[PDB]
Length: 59
Length: 67
Image (cartoon, rainbow over all chains, first blue to last red; front, side, top):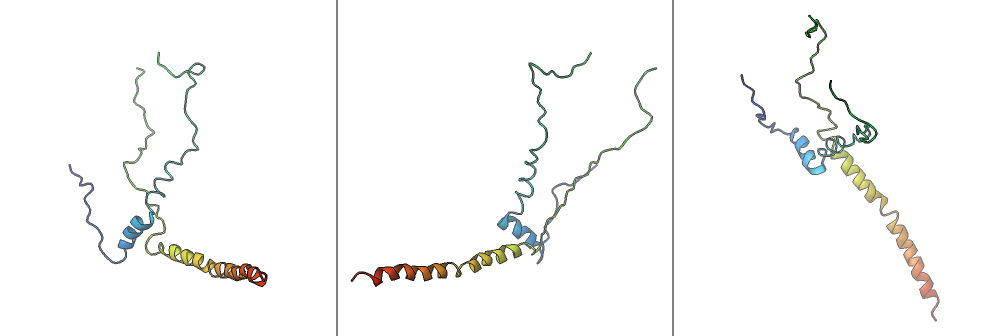
């Protein structure tokens, strides 16, 4: 069937521009999003120590 | 006879796409910016004027001697 993605007209009123004005000017974007999704560093590194450890196979 | 298809136990996982964790929007921002900015200016005039008081004190010792 259908789906129309990335197809949405803007708000264009008094208050909702302040959500798009604080975004560009003071960067509430790009740090709450992209500075937190990188860190996300505390997870365990899934590395195989190849001369000692070995991975799975199949019969 | 030992084939796969299980009787039950299913989800699924979503095809959904959403994480609107906002986030102090809509005039709540620009409010913590301005007040903390003038707070830094409020920290002035109690230090520069205070150092200005010591600045005349520093020049005082120069003028009192030197005859």
